Length: 287
Image 1 (cartoon, helix red, strand yellow):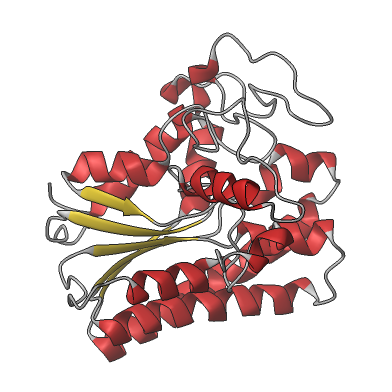
Image 2: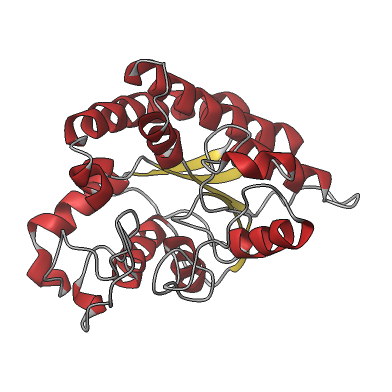
């Protein structure tokens, strides 16, 4: 039996990675390129929609639309749970991890209080895993998951400390079915990492929510995706594994029927999946 829906939302502040970013990596990398920052690249690239790391609006944009909320989207493609980004070359210019996004949000309030009615949306961790696997990180995966969890708890704590009261925190996605992970033969490692984060993080957040008197909702993206991928015809999906828009090793022409694909490229879902995700995330709130 379901409990009462949460109160409406009129403003979202979103923090996270390329599953949320609605233009920041594009803005920031154009700035870094203009400045001559060593190793900078234009992100996300040419085969993306309006600076999103997809072919359409991300889940949090859909959430905002669903709830009747304005969105300030601080998320940055490549963001890790800590201070920095998968793209190591960004750190000379800006700390664009979750912790750096929180810092910049709290430093730019311009003597206004944090809005106690704004929903602070947090969706991060995938790049902790991708960085670890692509650059031979030394932590055991269980320890990396522990750091990811601690980093996300610290963000909620620091936002609350400053006056935030309302949160939505997204679980790990199912990294084990990401095409780049399958291609890397890293399905078991992704399974282990994501299960450790998703077991531990909601326990840490329930403790913090009670201690600080927060309204905090947990979105289990793994349950969401498992249901989609077990019953794809119900949602009009046909292709669960092939990217619509191949980019690895090189860019190839996009599929003709992207609204029937799960994945846009080798790491990121399509606008259709983002739409279903945003609608599912909106389910806990009254309009």
